Length: 114
Length: 109
Length: 103
Length: 107
Ligand SMILES: *[C@@H]1O[C@H](CO)[C@@H](O)[C@H](O)[C@H]1NC(C)=O
Ligand SMILES: *[C@@H]1O[C@H](CO)[C@@H](O)[C@H](O)[C@H]1NC(C)=O
Ligand SMILES: *[C@@H]1O[C@H](CO)[C@@H](O)[C@H](O)[C@H]1NC(C)=O
Image (cartoon, rainbow over all chains, first blue to last red; front, side):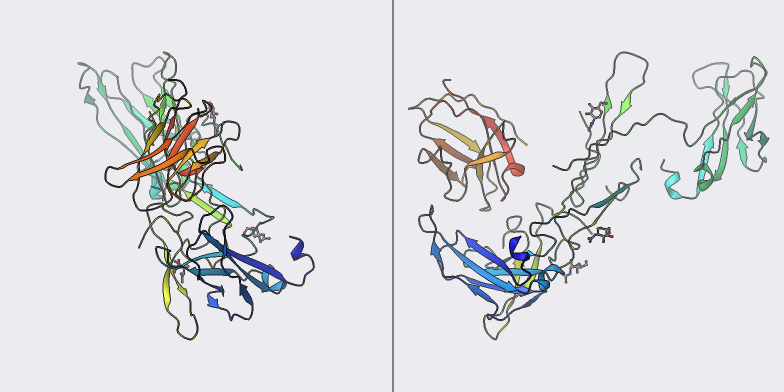
């Protein structure tokens, strides 16, 4: 929250935990198209405190502050061996990550019906 | 309820059972004035399957489906020579059933 | 004691009914309507593509209750994710619902 | 939704193993002790290497694809292990439980 107050930049972090062994592939997509490695930086796979041999890795993506407030959904897609499909992904936008508004307009009609 | 979801017509039935002898008369009133004979149909008396010497009838009034939707009474008047005043009547409305109390339990936790 | 009148699993409505056995009085019984809609509150417009605005409307006509909001636990939803690793682009099928289906 | 509440006795030396159903598709299978005060469910045993802090080193997981019983065993009983242990699957823990059962101390 305090990072989206200076109105300078926003950092979204993709954290992959529990994977073994190391050397996992991670990248970012912006509205269904990938980005160059000049805007996101991944970290080397480091060991895990409570795990015998499981690891973890971080991938930060920095974007302009106004590029995140208007929408512009970001996705992090990763590909480690162990995945049953070998590829998975997650996604965030301004309306999903720690929102301050549950704008609900649920309507229910034909309660009796047949 | 099933017949009103077709959004075409509404069918009200005046059921006259348990009278004796025959020759019962049925009319369909609305706000005092009667309805045309081409709006309702009356069947002939038939004997009761269990009761030996009694009868029954029916009287179907078919109206536009939307017209049922706004109040509108449709009271059925029956004349038979055994009634205390020779005339009886019944009425229904869109609102003619019960309280139907809603019991909403909206949850935000 | 309750008949499962509806067990919709794509909009998640769980309408049902029963007859409440009141006292041994004249039959002024009560018929139950335990409708139980569950709101996802965090799903997307299409359930199978995480790129659309999230979700404002929740329409429940109980006559078309016998596009969806939720995800069927026994069903699998996937997508094509356009990864590259350099110059080539192997558009590979991802999983939007890891654990409801396996390769 | 199975509720096979059994009365398996326990003690310090005593060991009790619960039985649970498995989908066998290598999902997340877990045993979870529900907390009455919290109103939520806290995983005591999971598919991963997680073990509850109170139950560290005294619990064992035992999976048979052959016989379709998913069973977990507790080495020692401190007599405080009396609660709703529910098994299950899916990533979720609370809303995913398949069968629940409450174990017991002494007898
Ligand atoms: C909240 O939802 C309503 C209903 O569609 C919409 O008109 C309004 O713009 C929404 N508010 C915001 C801030 O998006
Ligand atoms: C519905 O009414 C019954 C009794 O009339 C009550 O026990 C129940 O709590 C109500 N349902 C709610 C409040 O969701
Ligand atoms: C978004 O919704 C459309 C409409 O059904 C459907 O093709 C799909 O769920 C989504 N589109 C894509 C390209 O995935």
